[PDB]
Image (cartoon, rainbow over all chains, first blue to last red; front, side, top):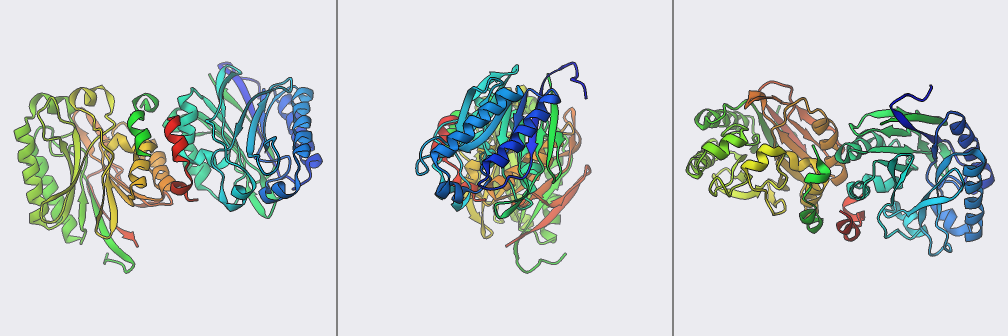
Length: 262
Length: 262
């Protein structure tokens, strides 16, 4: 509906099905979503993990060159600029195929990249064979009037990764994902816990549908700090648009002991 | 019912209302629960936080001497021995009133204390004024055919505390609690997440009813590693008896990076 008072940030999440190894098709679906999110007055669109190439780690390692990644990243910066909306996307890193990881990047409405993050927790033997894990904590930055951060799919399932973002001041954690297998415990149990245990909001943008040898779950969701869904999709392609409204674990935690016990 | 095959541990959780500063009354309710749990063939009874004195931190600090704690602890060891069942209880620590913390202790069916743990995360200004926080990680020990560990009430709400127990090999985490205020997100959201993110089972034994200026929630529960309740109580006094059946986060977590990011 119209932008409510007492809300000064409206975000959108794209949920759709990618065609593996067909970036012209997948980036046209991200351009359509960006145009639709911008027409609904969203200031930022979050899109799913590896969407531009499809979630096919082995095949990205084997067949997608650094030059082809950079072409897709240039088109994505063009879409943020041409549709006038900030975009968070997730592509392979910029290095050669044997040295790059999976990244997530946030570009503003000028198409300029403000923050980038390399996935620290790779999931399963295919990702682990195709990508180098990140070694840096998640970034946090002011945008739109709150502190945004980036994490990617399996990262959010480790409470340490979300606590690292919230300890650097994150209020809204944006998470491109690719979750298949009817894995109901990640959005149903873990995401609400990550929101409550840090007092943060998390946005989770998934694929859906048949892609890459999997059928993705959809179920994209924004969870607020009480653990409740601000908005949620089903199993089919859609665009979720939500307005964000305007115990103290992060202070009580005994971090100096905790870091010696992990 | 009867002990199922494919289960070799049956535990019990006591949920009841304590009368503050009346250990003869409260320890008689723990003796009745221990007798009932033993008659149901449970091998261990978990009882709620500070039950022997009531959950009244300010008044324990002001009025309960080290000698009175030790009298209650001696009676509790007698109950484990006389009712022939292992018991986990939670009392003030043994030191003087100005130096002790809140502890949880596990005694076997001989009344001998096998493990003790001092609460690391104190909750709210009253606990913080009445007790010294613990500085040690949770203990883990083999008993009954699996690795048991101890944590207490607010501790389990920090994912770091449960990850510390699971990193030392815990499979079953026993947690005396005192949760009031209709705090549905702790058993409904956080406990299932702690079970799933470590692949462990957690038992949470609460007070219920009017006690100490609060009305406790009850809702004692045992949650298994998929996050689902093995058994659960309502708001009234009861004894929950459950048989325990016979992603790899704990290996994938990048702990060396995580400990530098908290």
